[PDB]
Length: 371
Length: 111
Length: 56
Ligand SMILES: Nc1ncnc2c1ncn2[C@@H]1O[C@H](COP(=O)(O)OP(=O)(O)O)[C@@H](O)[C@H]1O
Image (cartoon, rainbow over all chains, first blue to last red; front, side, top):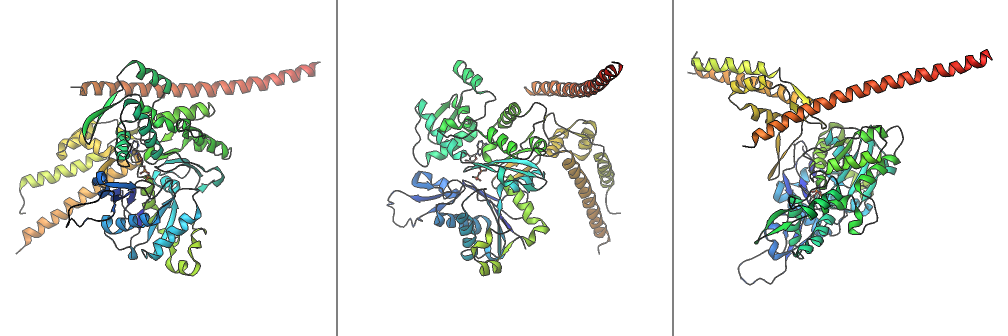
């Protein structure tokens, strides 16, 4: 039999089969409901659209995300998401397939327990397993040591691993990610008159971010370059027409990752939490960690982010070590790729949580050595 | 046997292309983990034999594209990975030509 | 028409990468040599002070 690999993430569902090179179903993790009245009798319209259909009916729906920061907040919505993923995108019967789920470090425990309970009671899968996103990223990267920085859409986290041993006291988790970058871009785009307030203009702003934003290698020099020239100013065409022109806020948006004070957060940038995780690890694995700094997740896809991260970590660490940043082109799907590798490993077929184990030990069996 | 002289010619040249695959040379990039070709001459001649473009085959070996849902994203490769891919390609094309030759033989024999 | 520009940039890039590699090689070489020479001179200098107090 084959196992499914559902990388829920927070803002993009990625599912597929264990043993493939890529997911076969990538769609947004949104659930939309109509907000207007509806006049044409016989239209027979539905009450809630899931996934990629909601993005077509944006102008009529209110789009809600069922996952805020890794954490699931709307369990009925999330159950709809899973039902859509199993039956409409993949077209499989979940009572014949083990399912490997992913989760971020340092989430509530009820999240994981309720996820297991759903997967066994509602969808009736034979086995299931919840994996950490950073470990799976390291599987897909081909390493066995290295400090991984998995910046998704809800959370950002560093997880240092050495020789296959993870150092839990050095795990860092930050709640700044692509969703906060989108909100900051919505906010600073009002300096030029453009206003995006609806829950469906957030998708337009996310598209603008993905297509035009980039990380500056030096922030003050790019500030001055934008103040003087106009060579970095680019245009974008809305779904309506009426092109908008983006100036220096092409690189002020992702700079929030290195200066979280822009959105009023207290914490330090990703370049500094990475270094603090290093310095919290031992002394005789720090050289390997410096040399194996692995990036994954969608928020690491900006142009120039690897070069910026290297410049910063190099200015932080001692001057005698080679600091190297691994940033594959298929970063966004690294967690899923690693999940497929892991679930196909023949050694892993004894780590599943079978259904009988659950029936006899309750949902608490998730936090056991299968953690 | 039933098959023409052009077909024997193509068989021989295909085997020579398989032979030309082995001498390809790849190096890591400047400050990255990506494979890039340094020697291009055997690449050019193997492409001229195979009926493909040399730059296009080199790009297809260094930067595969995979399907993620409804989009294509480029996958990264290092020297070991591209070498394993080259070997698997050669084994595949050889075994394919072999099976098809057996099909041709059986078609000749067929009553 | 810009493809010639692209190719020329690739060529100068390759040249600069080879240059950087050679400079790193010479750097690490000379640095090993300087460290080893300093080790030797410090050792033998301490030995000189020891034979000096010996003479005293
Ligand atoms: N090319 C890109 N540049 C900048 N941000 C991107 C790019 N592609 C995707 N993103 C951001 O990544 C986020 C999705 O990341 P993802 O890896 O899907 O995490 P998750 O699966 O947890 O949602 C989106 O919010 C989007 O804004």
